[PDB]
Length: 120
Image (cartoon, rainbow, N blue to C red; front, side, top):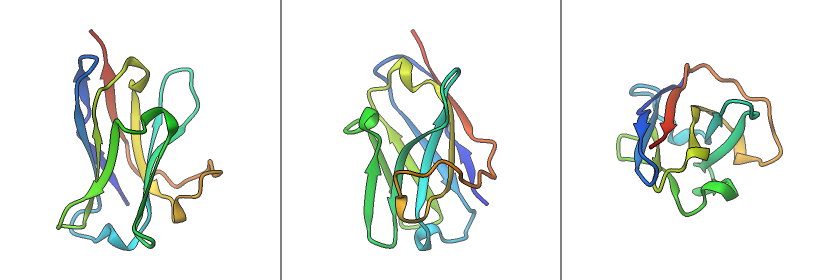
């Protein structure tokens, strides 16, 4: 049971910080993935934090621009998005992604996600 926020309208080159929260409940016991679904495109994995092996994964398209992390609270998983591009325009969702396994499509999405729009 995860809840996304932090979306909005941003100019190309700009920055947003998304959040994924389970409200006091501690997420550091789970592996969490960020996903997005853009218009005309299929659902895609963006980033994943592996809390069992203390590791992080990124799609080739966002490498070096996006960072996934938690703070001390440990109840929220953040997605820092830098140098945003139009191709990043999408609804962003989080979900449990055990082991951040790269070849999986089906996840349990309980959130409404949060919309990110990148335009001039």
